[PDB]
Length: 300
Ligand SMILES: O=C1Nc2nc3ccccc3n2CCCCCOc2ccccc2-c2cc1ccn2
Image (tube, rainbow, N blue to C red; front, side, top):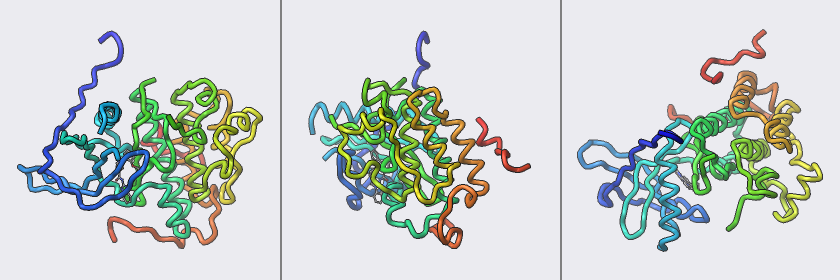
């Protein structure tokens, strides 16, 4: 082809009778998500699923199918994928169930049991998920802790491709300055958002710029104010957030560099995050010289 490569992803159409809704998991601007079970008729398999419907219009149906397009076209361990769609009167996106919910709610709920190893590994995994999106020439445009989901406490994935695009109400407090002032979105504007996301996690789910209305945020950033250093953050970790929030986009880190930096820190978590009572902390499992060293799997 002359331009971008052909997108040969498979959109799978699934029958209504192949799956069942069990209960509602949540509602909001993202839509309405149900817990369910998908049982492909031929095979002896049962697959836990999240089923998204909007809370119908021809406009609503366009937007939701644009989202399904993008979700069907991704394939990465730290990115939520579309299993299929069901074409009843209400269009339904069938997705992989993320049992522990969104990471923002998780950090708030399990604050007293989250240690530095988990926090840093989450940062790595999100950076990997985002770096994969960058490799696919795809800008998320809505990265936040509310859009990172928890498969297990050890494994998180990025989701919510409703604003996602190739290279209403908007998430002003997670957006780069240039996006606010000029609607410019790049991979490096996603980095700003990663910065904010990390701050959310390191503060155990604090609202950024809490009390400040969104219309004042642009002039605050112009003046040079940024989100403050969380109590548990070493200067090492805060410095990385601060780089994500530079005026010059190219001066911010690349996602591949963040994978490297956080993975180095993840080898010795207590050097980089100071948490009272750390590593006496337990979270549920499925079974329930050396400073600059980086494993090749993290060096892309
Ligand atoms: O498993 C998914 N959700 C889900 N599991 C839960 C378990 C416990 C309690 C609540 C739970 N929730 C609700 C979270 C909804 C907000 C974020 O989710 C999305 C927002 C936009 C588009 C897609 C998705 C999405 C959601 C799930 C899986 C793949 N994608």
